[PDB]
C-alpha cells in the first residue's frame, strides 16, 4: 500500500522502430490532489526517457540519484548512455537498498544510440530487470494498464498509431482508477525527433 | 620513522613551501595551457607534448575535460593527477547538482577544489598535486567566467591567463593585445593562435601539437565544442595569412 | 593516520614553526585595520594588480556576518579555509543562541582553532594573521588581531603582512582621538597609512568600511581616487 | 647505521643486527639451564643477588605458563614476564577452544611465531629474552623446547642460555640425560650450575630450581624444600 | 625531526620539558601571594603599543567564583587548559553539589599536562607539552590556597611564588619581605611593590592586572579606580 | 674505509638509482645466511624434496628439528633462510590452503598456493615498514591433469614452474648439476628420480652424508598425501645409489 | 601493522619524480615486450627469458586476460604484475556486476591509472615497477593502451617496453601501416621481437595474445611456431 | 649516535638508552627509604621543594586502604600509574570483594610498564615506585624501577645520595623484621637521616611517611604527626 500512498501509472511500449512512454500527472496525498502538473518522465538521454511510479519522495530521490550517477558516468566515459546500461545501473541502484528499498517501480524506454532499436524495460522496488518486447507498465494502475496493453498493442507500429494506442491506454486506464489520472503526459521517441503531448483527460 | 620521513607537509625556515614551489616549476616546464574570455564565449588552447606517430589519438581531448554540463577544464602537469582531480571535480559538481537541482556555479566548484587541495598540502604527509587547473564555464550569476588555480590552493579570477613555459611572455601578450569588453570570438581566437605560436616558439605552431576548445551560450544552453583538426588547420592558415599581411604592411 | 608531531619545542622553547608562519605572514600582502569611534575600516594592498584579472575572487576582505568582517595577511588558501570555518562558527553560534554573533567570541574561537592546529598531530598551524573587524550588540566597534601562534588581542588600530611593523609604528604616532570622529577622516588616515606601502596609491588598493550594523560595503574606486586627491590636497597645503 | 636501526631492514649482506643485539642482551644475562629426562624436565636458573635485602624467590626467572608447562627465561626479565603472560594467554585460549591442556609442541610453535611477529616491523623491536619451556604428558612424555629471541623453537635433550651456556652444555654431555631419573638429575643440575657459575664474577648468587614430569602428576611445580637443601649439599660436595 | 617527542636526555630528563621551562622564563612576569585573609594574583601586561586594548590583555582568568589563575608563557595555549579546568570544576559541582577544591583542580590540570605524543593515543590529541606556568589562587574549605602548576606536571602548593621573565631573584626578594602572619592588605602591598620594582617599564593601571580571592567574597578583579587607590600609597 | 650510504635507498626497500630494490635483493643473500641447501626434483609421476639435516649439537632433540613441513595432507614444503621466517611462512601457507579448501570446496592447487604466497611476499616488498621475510619456500604436490608439481616462492616473489631447482648457499651449483642432468638424461622413473635427487646433493655439497643427516619428503601418484622418508628408506636409497 | 602515512614518492627540487624515473629504469631493465594494433584487432607479444631449461616455461604464464575481451602484458617485475592484474580483474568484475555490461578497455585503463596514482601519492608503499600493454575490444573497435608506472596512460597504435625500447619504437614506426590486417600485425610483432630477442627466439620463449571481435585469446605454441615459420 | 634517540632501537652492547635515562631519572628523584617488619611496612620519604617557599610536595600516594606507594621521578607518570593501580584495586574490591594482593598488583604494573618498552614512539614511565602493602601474606615491599622490572625487597632506598641509606638497610636488615612499629619507623627515619649530609637536618617540616600494618590501614603522616616519631632521634652521624 506504500506504493499506492501517492498513486502512479507509467507505461512504455514499442513501435516499428520508435518508442512511446506515458505517465499520469496527478500528485497528492492518499486523499487530496495537490498538483496536477507533476513530472514523472525524466530524460536520462537524448533518446532515452525513464518513468517512475510509487512513493513520490522515493520517485524524486531515485531520479536525482540516478541523474547524479548517470551524468558522472557519461562525463567519465564520453558516450551517451546505452539503454541496457542505464537499466542495469538503475537496477543496481535499487538493489543497493535491499533492506531499505525505495517504494518505486520504474520503467525505462528509448532507442539505441547507434542502432535506434526500440528498448523498453521495467523494474520493481528491489530493482528486478524485466525486459519485455511488447510493453511494460507500472504503478497502482497495473492491472488496468496490463489489460489495456495486452489487447491494444500490436508489433511494428508507426509513430502516429503508436501514440494513439498509448494515449488511449492511459486515458482508459486512469479513468477507471481513483489514485491516478488528472492529466497524462506522453513522450514519443522517434528516430529523429521526440514529441511531448498532454492528453485531454478528465481532471477528476 | 623520524629519520626516514619526508615531512612534506611542514613549513620552511624562510617561510616558503618547497613542495609547492617545485610543483609550480614542474608545471612551468610542463605543457602549455591558455584561457581567454570573449563577450560571447570563452576559449581554451591546450598544447599536447607527446605527439608520437604511434598515438591512437582517438580521444576528443587530452588535457581538456568537461567538469559538468556547463563548465570545462584544462590541466597542466601530471596527467594522472589530472585524471583523478577531474573525476573528483565531476563527482562534487554532480553532488551540488543533486543537492540544489541547479548547475553548480564555477566559483563554487573552484573554491571547493582549492579547499581540498589546500587541505592536502596542509597535512596528510603526501606530496601535493603538482597540476595547475584552468577552469572555464557559464553560470547564472556571472555568465562566462574563468579561473586559474595553483597547487598551493590559491585561485584567481582572470579575463585571460596562461600557464606553462614563457608564462610571463604570454601574459604580456594578453595584456598588450586583449580588448577588454570588446573582444569577440574571432578576435579572441586570433589572439589565442598568436599566443600559441609565440609562447612556444620552439616547434612552431602545428595542428596536431595543440588542441582548441570553445564554450558558448546558445539558447540558454552551454555548448562546449572541440575544434577539429581541419579547424586547427584553418586557424593555422588564418594566422599565417594575417602575419604575412602585417609583415607586408610593415 | 598521519600523526607526526610537526609543531614541537625547539631549544629555548622557541616554536620555529610559529616563527616560519610569522615569516610567511610578513611576506604576504599588506592589510591594515582601524577602529574608529563610529566605524571600522579595513585596507588591503592589491599588489600586482595584473590587469585582465577579476579582482572579486582575490578580495582579501570577506564579511562573516551582517556585523563581522575580517582581512588576512599570509597564505591565501589557509585564509580561505579559515574564512569558511569562521562562517561555520558564526552560523553555529547564531543557531544555538538566536542572538547576533560577538566579534570577540569569533576571534577567540579562531584563535582556539589555531592553537589546536599548533597542538595537533600531523598538522601545521595556519600561517595567516587576521584582523577581525565588527560591532557588538550596542554598536561598539571592535578590532581584534590574531596571529598563527594563536594569541589574539584587541587593537584600536594595527597592520598585518608586508611592512606591518612600519605601518603600525606610523599609526601609533598618527592616531589621535579626534582624527577618527567621522568617516572621511578615518578613510584619509587609512589611505595615508597605506600610501607608504602601495606605489599606485589608488588602483592597487582596496578599502572596506563597516558602520554600526549598517550593511558594510566596499569603498568605490572613484571614492578611492577622489580621497587620494583629497589627501594630496592636504599634503600640498601642509 | 641503516642496517642496525630496526628489525624491518636487512644488512647489505642480509643480516638482522637488531636480533643480534637481542642475542647479546640475552647472553650477558644470568645463566639458565634446562634438562629433560625420560621421567621429567628440570630447570635451574641463576639469580643475581643485587643486595641481600632481596627475598629468596624474588624476581623469579621461572614462570608457570600452563598447568603442566614451565618457562625458564634469561635476558630482560620484564620482557620475560610479558612473554610468560602471552604464553599463558595462548594456553588459556587453547584450553577454551579445545577442552584440554595445550601440548608443548604447539604452544612453543605459537609462542615462537608470536615472537617472530614482533621482529618484522619497525613499530616494534625484537624481544630481549630467550626462554625454555618444559612439560609432560601421559602420551607424549617429558618434552622441552628452547626458543630464541629471533623466534626459533627446537626440542633439546638439554639446553643452556646465558653467559656460561656452552660450558654447561659441554660438561653435561657426559650425562646421558635422555634416559635418566629426574631426582638425581636435579642434583646434577645443581652441580653443573654451581661449576658454571663464576663466583669471582658474581660473588652473591642464588638458585631457583623446579621440575615437571610424571612424578608431578603432569603438572608444573617448584622443587620441594627438603630436596632443595639436599641438592644444594650435593652441589657443595661436587664443588670439591 | 630526528629527535622525537618522547626522548630523554643523557642525564635522564626530557629536554623538551626543559625547553618548555625556558619558554616559561620567556613569559610575562606574574606574582601570587597567599595569606590567611585570602590570596592575591598579579601580572604585568607587557603592552607592546598603546593602540593595543588593555581589556584584551588579561593574564588573570576566573576558574570559578572562588578560584583565580595567573598564566605565564604561551597565553594562547593556556586558554584551552583554563577551559578544561573550568569545565572539570563545574562537572565536579554537578556531580557532588559542592565547589571543587583548588588542590583537586590543580591535580586534574596536572593530569591534562604532559599528555602528548606522535602515536601514543587518539590522533586528535596533543603533540607538545603545555608551555604555561600557572598560579592557582583560591579559597575553599582549607582556607585560602595557592598552587604553582609547573608545565612538567609537578604541581606545587606554595604560599607565595613569582614566575615569568623575572621569576628568580624577584621570588627571593618577595620571600624576604614575606611573612607567615601578613594580612591581605599587606600581601597586595608587598606584591605590588615587588612587581613595580621588577617592572621592565614604567607601570600604571594599564600595565598590570590584579585580582584577589577572599574567604567571604568571591573572586574579584581589581578595577582601575581601586588599582590606583592601592598603588598611590606605593 | 669511507663506508658511505646513499640515504635510505640502501636502508629500506625504495627504488635505487640503478632501478633496483636493495632490501629485496639483500633477501637473496639472506637465503644464503641460513647455511642450508634445499634441492627439489620432480619425476614423470613423482616429486622428491631432498634436504640435508644439520645437527650442530647432539644436545638438541634432532628428531624434533625436522624442517620439512606438511602444509596439507598432499602438500609438503621446505624452506631456506631464517627459521622463524620459515615457520611463519609455513603457518601462513597452511592458513591460506585451509581457507581455499573451505571457500572453494577442493584442495588448493600448488600453483595457486605458490601464487598467493608470492603475492603476500610482494605485499612485504611493496610496503616500506616491514621486514620483507627473507626466506624461500619450495613446495610439492600431485595435480590431476598435470601430474607431479614442484613450486618455489621467494622473498622477491618471482616464482615459476620447474622440473627441479634449489635454494640455499649452493643453489647455483645445484642449478648447474640440474642443467647437466637434464641435458644428459630425460626419461625418469620413481627410482631414477630419487637417485638423481640424492646425487644432486651428493655431487654439489660433497659430504657423503649419513642417513640421519638428511630429511626427504616425497609425493607420488599412489597415495598423494605428502610422506617423509624415515631412516630405513634413506639408507635404502643411499645403498642403491652407492651400488 | 602501523602503516606509514608519509608518501615515499616526493617532488624533487626540479619537480621530477626521480623515484618514478627509477621505476621506469627498472621497467627498462626487465624483460622487453611489444604491442601493436591492426585495422581489426590488437596483438601483444613478449618474451619469457628464463634460466637453464630446468624451469618449466610452460607452467608459468606472462600474458594474462582480464575479461573475455581484454588482455594485457607487462614489462618489469612479476610480483607487482600479479597484484596489479588481480586488482584489475576485481575492478572489471565489479564494473560488470554494477552495469551488467563488459568493461570498456579505456575505463579499465583509467581505473588502473587511478590505482597507480593512489599508490604513488599514498604513504608506506612503493611505486609499481611495471609498464602494462593492454589490448581490448569493445563496440566493434580495437584498443591498445600504454600505462606507465607514473600512473599516466596513452592510447598507442604500437609500443615497445623494456630493453632497447626506443629502438623498438623506431622499428615499429618504420614497419607500421595504418590499415594492416591481423596477419600483418602478427608479422610485424614477431619481426620486432626477433630483431630484439638477443638469443634465437623459440616458440616456448614467445607468448602472444590476440584481441579482436571474437574476444581475447592467447596463442598456443603450435600456431605460435606456425607463425614464426611463416614469418622466418 | 642513533641508539639513544628511540625506544625501539637496540644498542650494540645489548641495552636501551631510554631505559638507562629513566633509571637515571629515578635516582635523580628525591630520597625515599622504605622497609618492613614481620607485621608492618612503612615508607619514609623526604619531600623536596623547588624553593624554601614551596611546601615540600607530597611523594607518598594513597592507592588503597591496605596498599601505599611512594614516587621518585616523573610526577605526572607516577600519578598516572597510581590512578591505574587504584583503579585495579577498586576493580578487585568490586569484583571479588577482597583486597587485591600486593604481589599481583606489582606484577600487573610491571606488565603494564612492559608495553612501552616495545611500543614505537612510546616512552617509559620515568618514575620508580616503592609499594608498601599488607595482605593475607603479611607486609610486602616492592620497588618497580622505570625499567619495567620490579624487585621484592625487605628495605629499599631510592633517590639521590641513597648509598648511605642502602648500606644502613643492608647492615640492619637482620633486625628490621623482629622490631616493633616504633623501632621500625625509627630505623627507616635514621636511614633517611644518613641519606642526607651532616650539615643538613632531618627537619619535621619536610619529611613524610606512609605506614600500613596488620590492623592499621595505610595512613600517611605529615610534619605535625611525624613529630612523635621524631622524638629521641640521634644527631647526624
Image: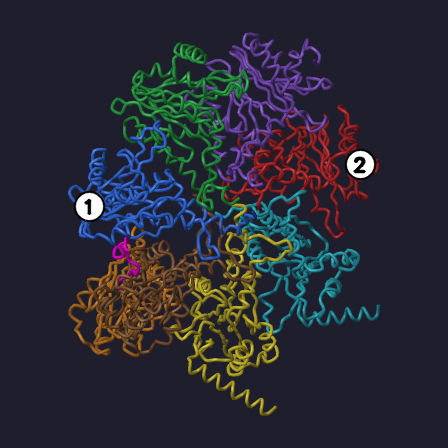
Chain colours: A orange, B yellow, C cyan, D green, E red, F blue, G brown, H purple
Seen from this angle, which residue lies furthest bottom? B249
Q: How many marks?
A: 2
Q: Quadrant of residue E211?
A: top right
Please report the bounds of the magenta region as a residue range.
Answer: G53-68
Question: Whole-percent x and y of residue C115?
Answer: 60, 47
Residue position marked by numbered label 2 in the rendering:
E230
User: On screen, A28 above or below B60?
Assistant: above
Is F74 or H185 nearer to us in this picture? F74
How many residues crowd mark 2 within 10 Å: few (<14), some (14–19), many (20+)? some
Question: Whole-percent x and y of residue D136?
Answer: 30, 22
- Assign the magenta stretch its main secondary structure: loop
Element at label 2? helix
Task: Give the CA distance from mark 1 to mark 2.
Answer: 111 Å
Question: Whole-percent x and y of residue F179?
Answer: 28, 52
Is H112 or F206 nearer to us in this picture? F206
Residue at 18 percent across and 76 percent down: it is: A156
Judge if badges 1 and 2 mark residues of a common chain.
no
In this orientation, does residue H62 appear? yes
Residue at 64 percent across and 18 percent down: it is: H164
Host chain of mark 1: F
User: On screen, H222 above or below G135?
Assistant: above
Residue position marked by numbered label 1 in the rendering:
F192
Host chain of mark 2: E
Element at label 1? helix
Amino acid at each position: 500500500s506504500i506504493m499506492s500512498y501517492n498513486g502512479g501509472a507509467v507505461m512504455a511500449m514499442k513501435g516499428k522502430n520508435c518508442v512511446a512512454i506515458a505517465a499520469d500527472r496527478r500528485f497528492g496525498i492518499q486523499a487530496q490532489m495537490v498538483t496536477t502538473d507533476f513530472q514523472k518522465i525524466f530524460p536520462m538521454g537524448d533518446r532515452l526517457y525513464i518513468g517512475l511510479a510509487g512513493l513520490a519522495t522515493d520517485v524524486q530521490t531515485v531520479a536525482q540519484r540516478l541523474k547524479f550517477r548517470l551524468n558522472l558516468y557519461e562525463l567519465k566515459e564520453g558516450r551517451q548512455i546505452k539503454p541496457y546500461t542505464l537499466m542495469s545501473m538503475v537496477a543496481n541502484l535499487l538493489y543497493e537498498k535491499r533492506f531499505g528499498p525505495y517504494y518505486t517501480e520504474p520503467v525505462i524506454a528509448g532507442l539505441d544510440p547507434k542502432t535506434f532499436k526500440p528498448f523498453i524495460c521495467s523494474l520493481d522496488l528491489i530493482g528486478c530487470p524485466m525486459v519485455t518486447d511488447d510493453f511494460v507498465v507500472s504503478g497502482t494502475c497495473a492491472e488496468q494498464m496490463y489489460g489495456m496493453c495486452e489487447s491494444l498493442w500490436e508489433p511494428n507500429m508507426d509513430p502516429d498509431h503508436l501514440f494513439e494506442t498509448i494515449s488511449q491506454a492511459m486515458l482508459n486506464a486512469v479513468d477507471r482508477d481513483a489514485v491516478s489520472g488528472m492529466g497524462v503526459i506522453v513522450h514519443i521517441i522517434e528516430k529523429d525527433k521526440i514529441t511531448t503531448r498532454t492528453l485531454k483527460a478528465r481532471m477528476d | 620513522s623520524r629519520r626516514y620521513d619526508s615531512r612534506t607537509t611542514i613549513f620552511s625556515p624562510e617561510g616558503r613551501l618547497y613542495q609547492v614551489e617545485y610543483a609550480m616549476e614542474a608545471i612551468g616546464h610542463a605543457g602549455t595551457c591558455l584561457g581567454i574570455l570573449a563577450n560571447d564565449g570563452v576559449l581554451l588552447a591546450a598544447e599536447r607534448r607527446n605527439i608520437h606517430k604511434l598515438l591512437d589519438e582517438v580521444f576528443f581531448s587530452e588535457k581538456i575535460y568537461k567538469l559538468n554540463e556547463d563548465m570545462a577544464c584544462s590541466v597542466a602537469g601530471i596527467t594522472s593527477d589530472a585524471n583523478v582531480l577531474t573525476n573528483e571535480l565531476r563527482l562534487i559538481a554532480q553532488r551540488y547538482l543533486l543537492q540544489y537541482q541547479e548547475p553548480i556555479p564555477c566559483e563554487q566548484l573552484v573554491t571547493a577544489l582549492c579547499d581540498i587541495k589546500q587541505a592536502y598540502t596542509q597535512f596528510g604527509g603526501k606530496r601535493p598535486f603538482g597540476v595547475s587547473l584552468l577552469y572555464i564555464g557559464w553560470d547564472k550569476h556571472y555568465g562566462f567566467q574563468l579561473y586559474q588555480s595553483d597547487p598551493s590552493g590559491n585561485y584567481g579570477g582572470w579575463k585571460a591567463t596562461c600557464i606553462g613555459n614563457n608564462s610571463a611572455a604570454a601574459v604580456s601578450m594578453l595584456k598588450q593585445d586583449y580588448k577588454e569588453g570588446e573582444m569577440t570570438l574571432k578576435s579572441a581566437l586570433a589572439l589565442a593562435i598568436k599566443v600559441l605560436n609565440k609562447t612556444m616558439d620552439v616547434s612552431k605552431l602545428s595542428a596536431e601539437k595543440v588542441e582548441i576548445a570553445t564554450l558558448t551560450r546558445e539558447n540558454g544552453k552551454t555548448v562546449i565544442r572541440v575544434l577539429k583538426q581541419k579547424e586547427v588547420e584553418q586557424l593555422i592558415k588564418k594566422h599565417e595569412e594575417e602575419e604575412a599581411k602585417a609583415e607586408r604592411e610593415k | 593516520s598521519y600523526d607526526r608531531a610537526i609543531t614541537v619545542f625547539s631549544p629555548d622553547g622557541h616554536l620555529f614553526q610559529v616563527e616560519y608562519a610569522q615569516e610567511a605572514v610578513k611576506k604576504g600582502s599588506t592589510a591594515v585595520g582601524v577602529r574608529g569611534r563610529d566605524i571600522v575600516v579595513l585596507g588591503v594592498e592589491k599588489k600586482s594588480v595584473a590587469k585582465l584579472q577579476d579582482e572579486r575572487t582575490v578580495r582579501k576582505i570577506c564579511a562573516l556576518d551582517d556585523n563581522v568582517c575580517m582581512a588576512f595577511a599570509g597564505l591565501t588558501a589557509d585564509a580561505r579555509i579559515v574564512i569558511n570555518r569562521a562562517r561555520v562558527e558564526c552560523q553555529s553560534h547564531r543557531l544555538t543562541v538566536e542572538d547576533p554573533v560577538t566579534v570577540e567570541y569569533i576571534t577567540r574561537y579562531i584563535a582556539s582553532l589555531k592553537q589546536r592546529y599548533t597542538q595537533s598531530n600531523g598538522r601545521r598551524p595556519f600561517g595567516i594573521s587576521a584582523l577581525i573587524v565588527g560591532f557588538d550588540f550596542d554598536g561598539t566597534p571592535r578590532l581584534y588581531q590574531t596571529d598563527p601562534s594563536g594569541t589574539y588581542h584587541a587593537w584600536k588600530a594595527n597592520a598585518i603582512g608586508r611592512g606591518a611593523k612600519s605601518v603600525r609604528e606610523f599609526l601609533e604616532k598618527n592616531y589621535t582621538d579626534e582624527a577618527i570622529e567621522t568617516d572621511d577622516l578615518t578613510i584619509k588616515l587609512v589611505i595615508k597609512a597605506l600610501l607608504e606601502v602601495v606605489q599606485s596609491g589608488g588602483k592597487n588598493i582596496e578599502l572596506a568600511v563597516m558602520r554600526r550594523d549598517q550593511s558594510l560595503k566596499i569603498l568605490n574606486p572613484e571614492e578611492i581616487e577622489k580621497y587620494v586627491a583629497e589627501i594630496e590636497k592636504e599634503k600640498e597645503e601642509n | 647505521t641503516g642496517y642496525d636501526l630496526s628489525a624491518s631492514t636487512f644488512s647489505p649482506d642480509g643480516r638482522v643486527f637488531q636480533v643480534e643485539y637481542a642475542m647479546k642482551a640475552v647472553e650477558n644475562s644470568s645463566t639458565a639451564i634446562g634438562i629433560r629426562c625420560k621421567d621429567g624436565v628440570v630447570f635451574g636458573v641463576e639469580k643475581l643477588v643485587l643486595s641481600k635485602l632481596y627475598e629468596e624467590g624474588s624476581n623469579k626467572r621461572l614462570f608457570n605458563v600452563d598447568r603442566h608447562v614451565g618457562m625458564a627465561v634469561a635476558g630482560l626479565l620484564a620482557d620475560a614476564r610479558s612473554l610468560a603472560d602471552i604464553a599463558r594467554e595462548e594456553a588459556s585460549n587453547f584450553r577454551s577452544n579445545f577442552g584440554y591442556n595445550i601440548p608443548l609442541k604447539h604452544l612453543a610453535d605459537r609462542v615462537a611465531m608470536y615472537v617472530h611477529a614482533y621482529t618484522l616491523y619497525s613499530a616494534v623491536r625484537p624481544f630481549g629474552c630467550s626462554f625454555m619451556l618444559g612439560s609432560y604428558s601421559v602420551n607424549d612424555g617429558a618434552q622441552l623446547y628452547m626458543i630464541d629471541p629471533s623466534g626459533v623453537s627446537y626440542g633439546y635433550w638439554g639446553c643452556a642460555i646465558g653467559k656460561a651456556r656452552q660450558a654447561a652444555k659441554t660438561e653435561i654431555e657426559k650425562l646421558q640425560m635422555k634416559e635418566m631419573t629426574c631426582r638425581d638429575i636435579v642434583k646434577e643440575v645443581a652441580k653443573i650450575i654451581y661449576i658454571v657459575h663464576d663466583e669471582v664474577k658474581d660473588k652473591a648468587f642464588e638458585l631457583e630450581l623446579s621440575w615437571v614430569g610424571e612424578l608431578t602428576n603432569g603438572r608444573h611445580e617448584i622443587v620441594p624444600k627438603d630436596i632443595r637443601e639436599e641438592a644444594e649439599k650435593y652441589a657443595k660436595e661436587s664443588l670439591k | 625531526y630526528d629527535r622525537g617527542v618522547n626522548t630523554f636526555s643523557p642525564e635522564g630528563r626530557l629536554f623538551q620539558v626543559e625547553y618548555a621551562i625556558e619558554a616559561i622564563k620567556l613569559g610575562s612576569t606574574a606574582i601570587g601571594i597567599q595569606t590567611s585573609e585570602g590570596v592575591c594574583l598579579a601580572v604585568e601586561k607587557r603592552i607592546t603599543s598603546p593602540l593595543m586594548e588593555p581589556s584584551s590583555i588579561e593574564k588573570i582568568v576566573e576558574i570559578d567564583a572562588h578560584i583565580g589563575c595567573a598564566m605565564s608563557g604561551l597565553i594562547a595555549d593556556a586558554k584551552t587548559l583554563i577551559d578544561k579546568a573550568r569545565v572539570e570544576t563545574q562537572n565536579h559541582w554537578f556531580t557532588y553539589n559542592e565547589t571543587m577544591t583548588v588542590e583537586s583542580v590543580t591535580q586534574a590540570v596536572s593530569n591534562l599536562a604532559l599528555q602528548f605524543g606522535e602515536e601514543d593515543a587518539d590522533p586528535g590529541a596533543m603533540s607538545r607539552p603545555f608551555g604555561v606556568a600557572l598560579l592557582f589562587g583560591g579559597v575553599d574549605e582549607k582556607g585560602p590556597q595557592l598552587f604553582h602548576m609547573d608545565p612538567s606536571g609537578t604541581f606545587v602548593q606554595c604560599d607565595a611564588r613569582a614566575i615569568g621573565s623575572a621569576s628568580e631573584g624577584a621570588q627571593s626578594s618577595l620571600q624576604e619581605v614575606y611573612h607567615k602572619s601578613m594580612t591581605l592588605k599587606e600581601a597586595i602591598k608587598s606584591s605590588l611593590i615587588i612587581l613595580k620594582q621588577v617592572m621592565e617599564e614604567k607601570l600604571n593601571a594599564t600595565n598590570i592586572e590584579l585580582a584577589t580571592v577572599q574567604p567571604g567574597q568571591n573572586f574579584h578583579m581589581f578595577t582601575k579606580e581601586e588599582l590606583e587607590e592601592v598603588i598611590k600609597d606605593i | 674505509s669511507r663506508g658511505s650510504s646513499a640515504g635510505f635507498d640502501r636502508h629500506i626497500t625504495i627504488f635505487s638509482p640503478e632501478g633496483r630494490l636493495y632490501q629485496v635483493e639483500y633477501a637473496f643473500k639472506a637465503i644464503n645466511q641460513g647455511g642450508l641447501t634445499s634441492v627439489a626434483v620432480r619425476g614423470k609421476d613423482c616429486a622428491v624434496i631432498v634436504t640435508q639435516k644439520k645437527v650442530p649439537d647432539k644436545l638438541l632433540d634432532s628428531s624434533t628439528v625436522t624442517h620439512l613441513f606438511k602444509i596439507t595432507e598432499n602438500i609438503g614444503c621446505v624452506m631456506t633462510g631464517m627459521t622463524a621466517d620459515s615457520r611463519s611462512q609455513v603457518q601462513r601457507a597452511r592458513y591460506e590452503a585451509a581457507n581455499w579448501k573451505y571457500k572453494y570446496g577442493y584442495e588448493i592447487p600448488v600453483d595457486m598456493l605458490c601464487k598467493r604466497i608470492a603475492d603476500i611476499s610482494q605485499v612485504y616488498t611493496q610496503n616500506a615498514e616491514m621486514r620483507p621475510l627473507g626466506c624461500c619456500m619450495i613446495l610439492i604436490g600431485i595435480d590431476e591433469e598435470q601430474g607431479p608439481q614442484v613450486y618455489k616462492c621467494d622473498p622477491a616473489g618471482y616464482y615459476c614452474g620447474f622440473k627441479a631447482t634449489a635454494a640455499g648457499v649452493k643453489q647455483t651449483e645445484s642449478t648447474s648439476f640440474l642443467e647437466k642432468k637434464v641435458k644428459k638424461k630425460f626419461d625418469w622413473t620413481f627410482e631414477q628420480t630419487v637417485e638423481t635427487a640424492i646425487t644432486c646433493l651428493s655431487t654439489v655439497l660433497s659430504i657423503d652424508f649419513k642417513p640421519s643427516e638428511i630429511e626427504v619428503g616425497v609425493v607420488t601418484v599412489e597415495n598423494p598425501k605428502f610422506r617423509i622418508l624415515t631412516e630405513a628408506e634413506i639408507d635404502a636409497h643411499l645403498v642403491a645409489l652407492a651400488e | 601493522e602501523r602503516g606509514y602515512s608519509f608518501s615515499l614518492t616526493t617532488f624533487s627540487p626540479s619537480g621530477k619524480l626521480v623515484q618514478i624515473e627509477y621505476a621506469l629504469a627498472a621497467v627498462a631493465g626487465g624483460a622487453p615486450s611489444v604491442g601493436i594494433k591492426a585495422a581489426n584487432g590488437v596483438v601483444l607479444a613478449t618474451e619469457k627469458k628464463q634460466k637453464s631449461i630446468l624451469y618449466d616455461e610452460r607452467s608459468v604464464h606472462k600474458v594474462e586476460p582480464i575479461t573475455k575481451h581484454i588482455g594485457l602484458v607487462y614489462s618489469g617485475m612479476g610480483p607487482d604484475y600479479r597484484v596489479l592484474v588481480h586488482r584489475a580483474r576485481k575492478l572489471a568484475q565489479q564494473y560488470y556486476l554494477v552495469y551488467q555490461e563488459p568493461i570498456p578497455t579505456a575505463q579499465l585503463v583509467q581505473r588502473v591509472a587511478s590505482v597507480m596514482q593512489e599508490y604513488t601519492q599514498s604513504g608506506g608503499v612503493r611505486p609499481f615497477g611495471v609498464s602494462l600493454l593492454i589490448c581490448g575490444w569493445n563496440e566493434g573497435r580495437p584498443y591498445l593502451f600504454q600505462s606507465d608506472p607514473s600512473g599516466a596512460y596513452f592510447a598507442w597504435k604500437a609500443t615497445a617496453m623494456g630493453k632497447n625500447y626506443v629502438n623498438g619504437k623506431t622499428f615499429l614506426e618504420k614497419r607500421y601501416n595504418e590499415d594492416l590486417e591481423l596477419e600483418d600485425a602478427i608479422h610485424t610483432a614477431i619481426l620486432t621481437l626477433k630483431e630484439s630477442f638477443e638469443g634465437q627466439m623459440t616458440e616456448d620463449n614467445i607468448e602472444v595474445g590476440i584481441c579482436n571481435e571474437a574476444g581475447f585469446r592467447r596463442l598456443t605454441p603450435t600456431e605460435v611456431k606456425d607463425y614464426l615459420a611463416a614469418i622466418a | 649516535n642513533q641508539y639513544d634517540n628511540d625506544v625501539t632501537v637496540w644498542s650494540p652492547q645489548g641495552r636501551i638508552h631510554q631505559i638507562e635515562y629513566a633509571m637515571e631519572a629515578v635516582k635523580q628523584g628525591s630520597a625515599t627509604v622504605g622497609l618492613k617488619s614481620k607485621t608492618h611496612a612503612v615508607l619514609v620519604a623526604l619531600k623536596r621543594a623547588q624553593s624554601e617557599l614551596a611546601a615540600h610536595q607530597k611523594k607518598i600516594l594513597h592507592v588503597d586502604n591496605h596498599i601505599g606507594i611512594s614516587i621518585a621521578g616523573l610526577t605526572a607518570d607516577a600519578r598516572l600509574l597510581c590512578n591505574f593501580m587504584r583503579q585495579e584495586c577498586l576493580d578487585s574490591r568490586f569484583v571479588f570483594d577482597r583486597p587485591l594482593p600486593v604481589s599481583r598488583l606489582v606484577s600487573l604494573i610491571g606488565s603494564k610498564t612492559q608495553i612501552p618498552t616495545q611500543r614505537y614512539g612510546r616512552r617509559p614511565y620515568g618514575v620508580g615506585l616503592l609499594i608498601a602493602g599488607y595482605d593475607d601474606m603479611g607486609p610486602h615491599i616492592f620497588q618497580t624501577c622505570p625499567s619495567a622490572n620490579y624487585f621484592d625487597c625487605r628495605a629499599m632506598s631510592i633517590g639521590a645520595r641513597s648509598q648511605s641509606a642502602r648500606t644502613y638497610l643492608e647492615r640492619h636488615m637482620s633486625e628490621f623484621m623482629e622490631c616493633n612499629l616504633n623501632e621500625l619507623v625509627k630505623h627507616g627515619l635514621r636511614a633517611l637521616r644518613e641519606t642526607l649530609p651532616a650539615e643538613q637536618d632531618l627537619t619535621t617540616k619536610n619529611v613524610s611517611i606512609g605506614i600500613v600494618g596488620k590492623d592499621l590501614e595505610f595512613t600517611i603522616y605529615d610534619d605535625d604527626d611525624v613529630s612523635p616519631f621524631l622524638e629521641g632521634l640521634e644527631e647526624r652521624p
